[PDB]
Image (cartoon, rainbow, N blue to C red; front, side, top):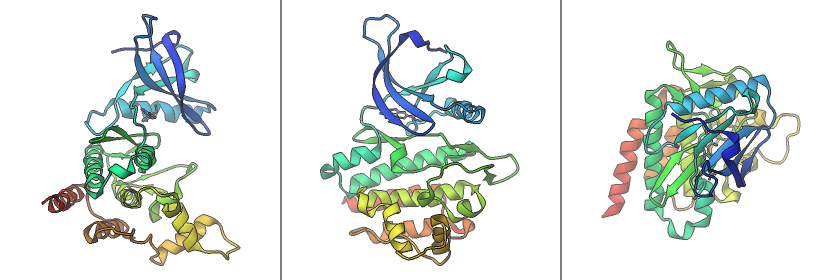
Length: 292
Ligand SMILES: CCc1cc(O)ccc1-c1ccc2c(C(N)=O)n[nH]c2c1
């Protein structure tokens, strides 16, 4: 119901950058009196026909979503042609859950951690009904609205399942977050609802270590690979470690019932991992049992 144009978009400050794109804070101001609404804006640095095509698919996915725990779509800008396309989304002042939690950690207890966990489960349950696979679940990619609510973000790798099958195979892997990936994703490039469940397991580990740098997944796995070899790639060493049942340890002070959920999510067999339905019920019941 509304298209945006270049001449009313005003730069305020930087929010982030990668190898192919960047994000900015701007004010849309068509009356030119500085009363306009503040928004967040994405654009591409290096436009290859391939990357430009992936960008337009990201936008169609975002249009179709409406849920309390998922980030809101606003519009698009074609003022300078297809090769200079921009995306407009809602601005959330508190930023990412990774950044927020490091800052305000002395006011966040085990009960609060489980509130965030529950809301993430509800969001993924909704994506499942549309047959979408997220592919990039991590605390850097969740956003905060206020002290009692969070939403799922960055949909830049998301895919749709075929009508006939229960997995999608990706042609040409990109630059990947290997320390959050399932084994059959690493060896065969297969992604599914089940591989999203392995990733949710690692998010729960991030939360109960309070996002400390020195206990992060990259730090722990590199420690476990060791000091010697010598002769192989880093990803080759990781695939071998996982085949022989090596896993991340229990965080200091983690409850029995929460640690059991982690171990179940990290099963080698895809057919033996739990559902997002059951995960929501179990988490809510544990939170109630701490209440009284
Ligand atoms: C436009 C980029 C984007 C793309 C996507 O697919 C999902 C979410 C975002 C996004 C990223 C960051 C923020 C922020 C902040 N404060 O950093 N606020 N709203 C944001 C939305």
